[PDB]
Amino acid sequence: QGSCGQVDIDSVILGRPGAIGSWELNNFITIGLNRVNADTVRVNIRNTGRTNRLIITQWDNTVTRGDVYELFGDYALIQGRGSFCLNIRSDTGRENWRMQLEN
Ligand code: NI
Ligand code: NI
Ligand code: NI
Image (cartoon, rainbow, N blue to C red; front, side, top):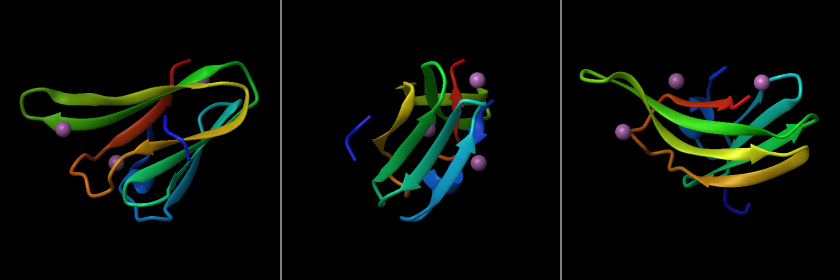
């Protein structure tokens, strides 16, 4: 985090500057994603329940390994509303970005 089941988030990660999305992950937690520029994605969190955790992965299907992920990062989600920024270039060859709650 820098200063400002599994859902498909490619629309924002691989989108243009200005690309936005919102996902209700459970009854308590909603995550907004906003691509602020070519280098940075902003994550917005609203959590009306207990602390949880957001896990971000990027998936590939390779001939040798089949469906496998690279862990990008994982982030505490405390009660209330907040934000943090991630350094992810949109011009990446990495596709199939996902996020999920730990619990
Ligand atoms: Ni890779
Ligand atoms: Ni996808
Ligand atoms: Ni949950």
